[PDB]
Length: 168
Ligand SMILES: Nc1nc2c(ncn2[C@@H]2O[C@H](COP(=O)(O)OP(=O)(O)O)[C@@H](O)[C@H]2O)c(=O)[nH]1
Ligand SMILES: [Mg+2]
Image 1 (cartoon, protein in one colour):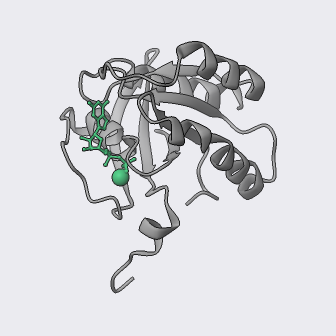
Image 2 (tube, rainbow, N blue to C red; image 1 turned 135 degrees about the vertical axis):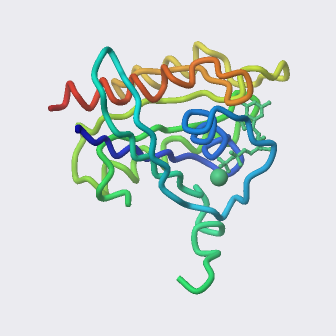
């Protein structure tokens, strides 16, 4: 069975964990420890093809990342770059995560999708047009999602898988 290692990155609080849990477990989580980084697997069918999705949900903040206990970006085949549409700071930070991915992969050609999450919220501050302009400058798809309503959730992950299949 074909395996796809996807990595979800972005600023703290944008919904990386909520997006992952919604895709895998079909439930919206109202809170999820921001320091929890883990892989979540689920068998899906995308465009008729069976595959095993391995999703690495990252913390997004060095503060949360190192908040460990008694205990990759390298192995990831595609990346979801998430901001929240009611979080201008998370959008302003997207370039940092984009540069991180290219550095850790030593490539300009990495499968990647820009995700604008929380589109169920009315207090929007990032316009769809400006997120689209940013995605065009990277040459990557832009997808609006809501981990709460499920809008765009499958589409964001499936598009990333399709970008990986295109990348061979
Ligand atoms: N209304 C709404 N809230 C969301 C959405 N996605 C995440 N949240 C909330 O945003 C907060 C942070 O989400 P979380 O997944 O922990 O963000 P993370 O730090 O990037 O993993 C949580 O309280 C979630 O319930 C969404 O699409 N819509
Ligand atoms: Mg999280």
